[PDB]
Image 1 (cartoon, rainbow over the protein chains, first blue to last red):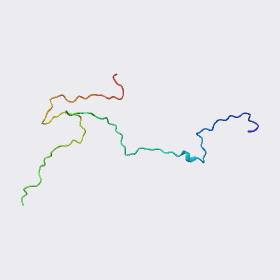
Image 2: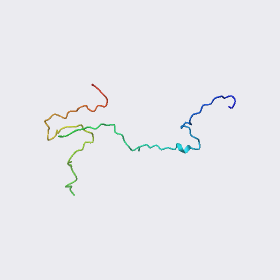
Image 3: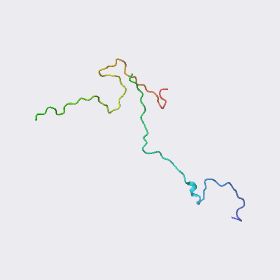
Length: 50
Length: 50
């Protein structure tokens, strides 16, 4: 590394990388709606009896 | 002893349809002389015939 490499390139640390110690920063919450919900596939029909 | 009253045929005030019904006019003791309700194909999600 010291003798056989001539030039080096440096960039800001990508934010996607994360050390193993900071694994709790990856904790996140996702919400799924209740399974009792029923989604209608039938259209509404409009009528009058007058 | 002799049976004077043991149940019998019982009249019902109204019948209740357990199936969904299309819109309609009166066709019982009252008969409607007007045209039956016109069914129009509207609120089409995708374009057709235009």
